[PDB]
């Protein structure tokens, strides 16, 4: 089930 | 040398690739700020352009719901972007603590976010990194003002002209057009507003997966839904505005100006 978590930004494509 | 003279550094608020944000005090004024400290020692020409871009965009934006640049100071080996300090913490923290907002509280919150976004768009600025972590509360008092922050990924656009400006943003908030690697512009910010509004009302995001490739597949397809029990008492007008924000086709996606006239925001 979907969770509210902090996430970092990407400034380029990351697989 | 205006920074070393006038200002004292205190605790770290956050950290980037070549940068740090720290509370600072302009000592003789008795006033506290957020100093973004960029280490410019052997910085590439591209990374200089990105510092100058952020400086230019931050100077441009004067709005009650946008963090205000107070000063920009170039010293030998460090650049200082001094911003008014916002002390109420991140919208992210407040959602987690409160679990979710009431429709009234959510509408008032999203209304201020849309006014910040509208101002950016009117000034030829696309943020690209909208999310609850990048929205700061003016105080810990209920209904305190929301301020758009962190223009590190922001771009300048020429009117309604769109292009492939490259891949940047935060996974859960990325628009389909950025993930498809197709031309994009101001609408990416409205997609993120839809993710934020969704989170405000039930306190969990519309797109989530342990597998990033599966997350991107769900976002590109607009595969969100309104499950029981948390959506059981949410108005259809709230759902309508979310649907218009989370529209795959950015040409058909609601704009900031249009969103601010939606009844769920304006008839209130
Ligand atoms: N005026 C301000 N007052 C208080 N805190 C601020 C202010 N401006 C920025 N911050 C804080 O500085 C930090 C910014 O670093 P952060 O890594 O979160 O930036 P970002 O570009 O959004 O990167 P990421 O994509 O990883 O979130 C955050 O903790 C944010 O709350
Ligand atoms: Mg941030």
Image (cartoon, coloured by chain):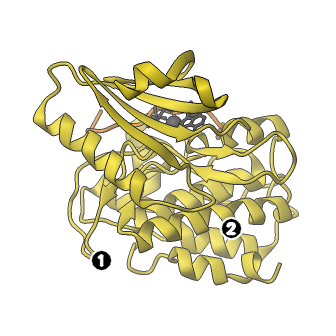
Chain colours: A orange, B yellow
Report crowding for label 2: few under 14, some 14 to 19, many 20 or more residues within 10 A (C-alpha).
many
* Callout 1: chain: B
Q: CA distance from mark 2 to mark 1?
A: 23 Å
Residue furthest to the left: B45
Q: Does the residue at mark 2 contact the one at mark 1 (Cβ under 8 Å)? A: no
Q: Which residue is mark 2?
A: B111
How far across and how far down the image is residue B187, in percent?
42, 68
**Mark 1 residue element:** loop
Q: Is residue B33 left or right of residue B102?
A: left
Q: Is residue B244 left or right of residue B155?
A: right
**Which residue is at 40% across, 47% downward?**
B216
Residue nearest the observer in this picture, B87 or B77:
B77
The image quadrant of residue B161 is: bottom left
**Which residue is at 25% across, 70% downward?**
B162
Residue nearest the observer in this picture, B41 or B226:
B41
Q: Which residue is mark 1?
A: B159
How far across and how far down the image is residue B17, in percent?
33, 24
**Which residue is at 49% across, 49% downward?**
B173
Residue furthest to the front: B28
Tag 1 or tag 2, which sits nearer the N-term? 2
Q: Is residue B242 left or right of residue B170?
A: right
**Mark 2 residue element:** helix
Quadrant location, the N terminus of chain B: top left
Position above or below: B147 against B80: below
Q: Are marks 2 and 1 on the same chain?
A: yes
The image quadrant of residue B152 is: top left
């Amino acid at each position: 089930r979907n969770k509210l978590r902090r996430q970092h930004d990407y400034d380029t494509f990351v697989d | 040398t205006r920074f070393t003279e006038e200002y004292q550094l205190f605790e770290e608020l956050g950290k980037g690739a070549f940068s740090v944000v720290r509370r600072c005090v302009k000592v003789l004024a008795g006033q506290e700020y957020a100093a973004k400290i960029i280490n410019t020692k052997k910085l590439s020409a591209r990374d200089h352009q990105k510092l100058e871009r952020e400086a230019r965009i931050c100077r441009l934006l004067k709005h009650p719901n946008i963090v205000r640049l107070h000063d920009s100071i170039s010293e030998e080996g460090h650049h200082y972007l001094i911003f008014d300090l916002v002390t109420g913490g991140e919208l992210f923290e407040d959602i987690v603590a409160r679990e979710y907002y009431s429709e009234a509280d959510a509408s008032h919150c999203i209304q201020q976010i849309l006014e910040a976004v509208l101002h950016c768009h009117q000034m030829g600025v696309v943020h690209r990194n909208l999310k609850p972590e990048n929205l700061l509360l003016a105080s810990k008092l209920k209904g305190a003002a929301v301020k758009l922050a962190d223009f590190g990924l922001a771009i300048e656009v020429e009117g309604e002209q769109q292009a492939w400006f490259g891949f940047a943003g935060t996974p859960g908030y990325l628009s389909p057009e950025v993930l498809r690697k197709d031309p994009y512009g101001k609408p990416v910010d409205l997609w993120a507003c839809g993710v934020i509004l969704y989170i405000l009302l039930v306190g969990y995001p519309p797109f989530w997966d342990e597998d990033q490739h599966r997350l991107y597949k769900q976002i590109k397809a607009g595969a969100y839904d309104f499950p029981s029990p948390e959506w059981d008492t949410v108005t259809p007008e709230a759902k309508d505005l979310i649907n218009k924000m989370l529209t795959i086709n950015p040409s058909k996606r609601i704009t900031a100006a249009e969103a601010l006239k939606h009844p769920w925001i304006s008839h209130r």
